Picture 1 (cartoon, rainbow, N blue to C red):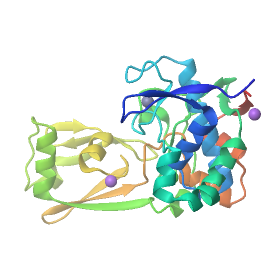
Picture 2 (cartoon, rainbow, N blue to C red):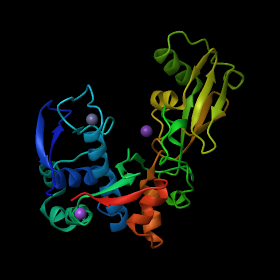
Picture 3 (tube, rainbow, N blue to C red):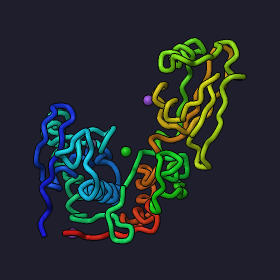
Picture 4 (cartoon, protein in one colour):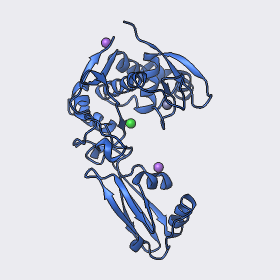
Length: 285
Ligand SMILES: [Cl-]
Ligand code: NA
Ligand code: NA
Ligand SMILES: [Zn+2]
């Protein structure tokens, strides 16, 4: 068959528009992964992005956009940069010499999706892991046979592998009180009141105690704008330091891991079968 025409919801304008699968996917790669990544990582990424649309088509419509299979909000579906936007911000030379690589990666995987028992998977992906990916159930609510923790030994080379953020004790309590009106916490005794309660083997903080409150690592990531929910806290004199590992949710495919694998000679099928446990590739058209 031919490549489908899909409905894409523009989260800024509120208008839904028809797009050829290929054009949509090029916009997703431009937004998710740079044209500087290896072609095999870009191919892996294109298959994941295509699979996401197919999965969405085969499952329940969302309330955010019931009349569109996907939207342009990276917080809900996946990133998307339009051609006009890319041309205006990067220029014609970038379109002809760099965006062409993105176009070739997408065309190069025409109609290919990742499958588990012959059905499109939920192909979660993120920037950089802590060295191991996360099982879906330690981050999200459900377990999926293809979203299992795997080693990701090349993520250590990512510029987002490690990060640190210093916050004054005063700003730390002020920020928490603003987000949680019931919190009882003392600016002068933070090291005695704040402690990690539950975390996965990969490292995502599931439960953290802050005075009388229990929050998730994701809650903390959100309040303090951290790169991930995998962190540790150092208590200083008058301040705390968040020491953060990786970037993103940690489930499914690591983008920097795919890049590292590509550099080592792995091809996109092997990258995909590594991150998505017991999966195959299917050409639907
Ligand atoms: Cl990236
Ligand atoms: Na194909
Ligand atoms: Na940030
Ligand atoms: Zn969406």
